[PDB]
Image (tube, rainbow, N blue to C red; front, side, top):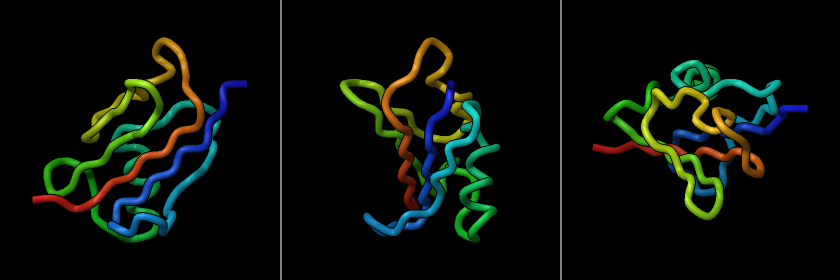
Length: 88
């Protein structure tokens, strides 16, 4: 129970996949941002250098780090896929 695949690619490329581990069910903020970035070896922290966007469905998208698992707080929604890219 409580399980979802979380993917994170902070390096352009609209196809190249980076992360996608279905951890138990709890992770997102800088903690997860490091598992996908610090892991491979690309940009770090989605602060201002670059931004991300968690696509869900209907109307539920997140952006910028500090996302404290914003999702299980009250429920869930299909799988989790976050795409990040450089910025200013």
